[PDB]
Length: 42
Length: 128
Length: 46
Length: 155
Image 1 (cartoon, rainbow over the protein chains, first blue to last red):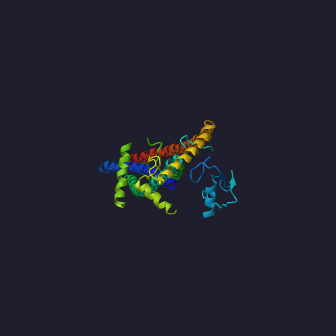
Image 2: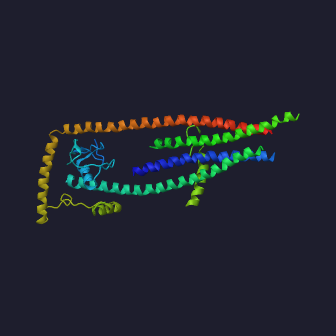
Image 3: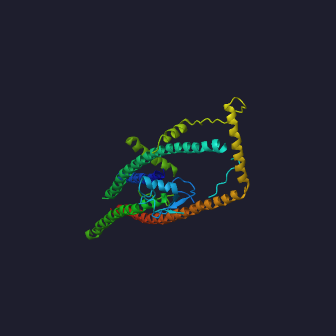
């Protein structure tokens, strides 16, 4: 039980930490997206 | 104060010298007979190696010792051990959902590391 | 046990985050050293 | 991998991140016969029936019944004997286990501190690493926006 309870706890916490990794990068792709739009027009 | 095999309070505790873990005499000697090792740290242990080291207040209503006390000891053992087998099958299901979403997230990070780093490079290319 | 391995993973990824920005900081310095020479060549054309 | 929990201080972006994880997961799609009845009695969840002479409450039904009555006597003499050696002390054997339960209980609340001091000794160290990377990433982002506007002014 407690062998995989660590393997349950360390997995979900590293998942939520990696869930934040996407949330930064999805907004970094966005700020790279709209800047290239406003400049390539001008 | 407790045993490290069943989770009891031993009346005759024994200490092994290779890993200091206090266990009951019949519980430590039984493990050494079946598989020739200390169970906790998986080191070698014998019966002659171990070192030998509680008040139970009887209820006033002590036929209760035959009928009412004897059944519930075999009742609380079964419906806990059956409850535990439901816990072990459910957690490996929750392990399979932990591992799948972990691989599902890393493919997003591996896909978004290719998206952002090229878009910032295209910001360095547009000036030229 | 959670904070035991959470420090374990975060200590290795700190350099990998910093070096990716450091390599991105080197390429932006290469444009800044490259663009200024063209404005230096305008006063020689005068 | 590197995502800072301390310095980054929305639940909607968690819900924004949870869909994209799901959109990739929508794609990726030893004992004897004692072990048999202890499983079977628990699954059926039915208590086993018990029979007692007292419950029957029958006197002189026949000859077998007469034998059953005797069983009542030597159990009550033994119960009065066990009620005799319990009433001899009757407070002193019960008080020595109450102090026994006090010394057993404090060890767990001793173990409640040793984890709690050590787990915050983990988070105290990572937060210093959490603030160092945010300092270096800020000067990286500060130098990043400067170069993006320098090269436009240079051209």
